[PDB]
Amino acid sequence: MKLHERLRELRSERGLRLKDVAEVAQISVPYLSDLERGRTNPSLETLQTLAGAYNITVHDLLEGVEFTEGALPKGLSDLIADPTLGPQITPDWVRTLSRIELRGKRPRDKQDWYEIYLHLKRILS
Amino acid sequence: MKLHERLRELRSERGLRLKDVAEVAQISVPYLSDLERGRTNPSLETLQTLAGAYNITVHDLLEGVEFYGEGALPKGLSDLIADPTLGPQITPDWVRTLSRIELRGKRPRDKQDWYEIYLHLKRIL
Ligand SMILES: [Cl-]
């Protein structure tokens, strides 16, 4: 969702008036209201202020929300993300693998990437 | 952890060089480095750019980081409305109703405590 919708949801579902939030944060009602409208976008340090008064972390505040590209191919990133599998792979091995492309084509998903990683490791060792 | 370390972790664990991450994002190589060492913090517009460039979301990117700098509700009262299975069934104005229960500033601690009272009182009213 949008961030202004989320910031309004957190206070309304919690039964709080703008003033209640205003006072516990170091913030005013017009500015907070602008933020819950979404004219302004807040600093991270304003988001701390809001999180802390909602008794929520800033990670958790940003749960339902959304607001580019990608520097590795997505399957390669998924492999880096796998908990059991990923960590065993050198930072080097990621950029080495990442250069593998045939005119656009790339290994599709992480066990594709994992597969050739294993073959390639034997050869380059 | 801290947001500058996290931003340095993502690029380091993917064997990426600053210009990689600077080339898919609007930012400059110098600006990224100042983000990564902690000198200034990025906007939310900037955060999203980096996150997608690491193929994760902004929520996930802040999985780990934390910030420093008071609550408008009791913690357990918040913990309850944040509970996904137990929390949406409670209305904003049951939430207000609960918060006025304190004796000497002493309050129900955990959400089971807040829930226990909600069930009794909701039956009385
Ligand atoms: Cl080619």
Image (cartoon, coloured by chain):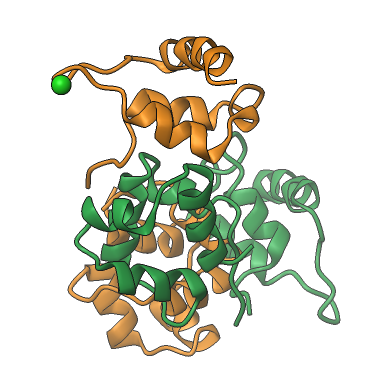
Chain colours: A orange, B green
Q: Is residue B84 above or below residue B23?
A: above
Q: Position of residue B6 (x, y in %)?
A: 54, 58
- Note whether B70 is above or below A87 in the view shown: below
Residue at (69%, 67%) from the top-left corner?
B74
**Is residue B71 toward the left or the right of residue B26 in the image?**
right
Picture residue at 66% right of the left edge, 53% below the top:
B79
Q: Is residue B9 shown left or right of residue B54?
A: right
User: Is residue B64 visible from the viewing direction of this image?
Assistant: yes
Q: Residue at x 55, y 50 (%)?
A: B63
Is the residue B32 above or below the residue A124 in the image?
below
Quadrant of ligand 1 in image? top left
In this rendered view, identify the residue nearer to me: A41 or B73.
Answer: A41
Q: How far across and how far down the image is residue A113, in percent?
A: 43, 17
User: Quick one: quadrant of the N terminus of chain B?
Assistant: bottom right
In the rendered image, the vertical position of residue B112 relative to residue B43, given as above or below = above
Residue at (72, 47) in percent of width and height:
B115
> Is residue B43 in view from this perspective?
no
Q: Quadrant of residue B48?
A: bottom left
